[PDB]
């Protein structure tokens, strides 16, 4: 493992050092999105939760193609408000149910420290 707790206050600073391999050492799912919702990074824990193969989803649009069940005010609407504002820090439960067994999770979206990119962190509940 990497030693980082889900929901940690300074998670964006800790995950700024991780390349894709390091991200694969987290205890929770982690996705890095650009401001349009294209997938930049997608770790092994997330693939275990959702069934997606990480290298096959990087470059895809999370809200349009990968995760249409999240294209809603309750998930994508929060994301795009945060992108537009340039600030995002929200944690909520959600169900992932697209071409998969419905899976209840806790989601934490947080703007990355540098640049303009956005983390989506996920764990089972
Ligand atoms: C709903 O369509 C959710 C889909 C989904 C969520 C999270 C992922 O990493 C992959 C697909």
Image (cartoon, rainbow, N blue to C red):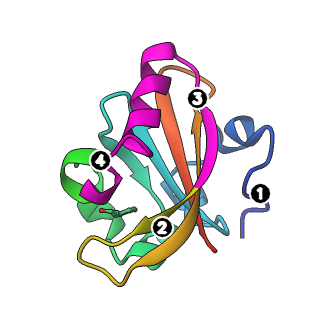
User: Would the CB of label 1 be found within 8 Å of ligand 1?
Assistant: no
User: Label 2 to label 4, Cα distance in Å?
Assistant: 18 Å
Residue 61 in sight from this viewpoint: no
The dot on residue 4 is 1
Among numbered discs 3 and 2, the one appearing first in the sequence: 2
Observer-nearest of 115 and 63: 63
Mark identifier at residue 88: 3
Measure how far apart labels 1 and 2 are at the Cα level: 15 Å
Residue 53 in sight: yes
How many neighbours does mark 4 have within 10 angstroms: few (below 14), some (14-19), or many (20 or more)?
some
Picture residue at 35% right of the left edge, 65% below the top: 54
Find numbered disc 3 in the image and state the secondary structure of the residue it sits on: loop
Quarter of the rendered structure image containing ligand 1: bottom left
Coordinates of residue 117 in the picture (x, y in percent)? 47, 30
Check if residue 8 falls in the magenta segment. no
Q: Give the labeled residue for mark 2.
A: 46
Q: In which quarter of the image is the N terminus?
A: bottom right
Q: Give the range drawn in magenta.
A: 67-92
**Residue that numbered label 4 is attached to:** 71
Category of crowding for the residue at label 3, using alpha-carbon neighbours closer than 10 angstroms: few (below 14), some (14–19), many (at least 20): some
For image coordinates 33% across by 72% down, the residue present is: 97
User: Residue 83 in magenta?
Assistant: yes
Identify the residue at image location x=40%, y=74%: 50
User: Which of the 4 image quadrants contains residue 98?
Assistant: bottom left
Q: Do the residues labelled 2 and 4 touch (CB within 8 Å)?
A: no
User: Which mark is first along the chain, 1 or 4?
Assistant: 1
Which of the 4 image quarters holds residue 81? top left
Instruction: Classify 10 Å Cα crowding around label 2: few (below 14), some (14-19), many (20 and above).
Output: many
Among numbered discs 2 and 4, the one appearing first in the sequence:
2
What is the tally of numbered marks visible in this picture? 4
Which is more N-terminal, label 3 or label 1? 1
Cβ of mark 4 under 8 Å from ligand 1: the answer is yes
């Amino acid at each position: 493992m990497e030693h980082v707790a889900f929901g940690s206050e300074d998670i964006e600073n800790t995950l700024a050092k991780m390349d894709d391999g390091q991200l694969d050492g987290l205890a929770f799912g982690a996705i890095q999105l650009d401001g349009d919702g294209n997938i930049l990074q997608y770790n092994a824990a997330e693939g275990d939760i959702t069934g997606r193969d990480p290298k096959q989803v990087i470059g895809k649009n999370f809200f349009k193609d990968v995760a249409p069940c999240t294209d809603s005010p309750e998930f994508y609407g929060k994301f795009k408000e945060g992108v537009a504002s340039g600030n995002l820090n929200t944690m909520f439960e959600y169900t992932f149910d697209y071409q998969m067994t419905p899976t209840k999770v806790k989601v934490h979206m947080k703007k990355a420290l540098s640049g303009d990119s956005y983390w989506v962190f996920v764990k089972r509940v």
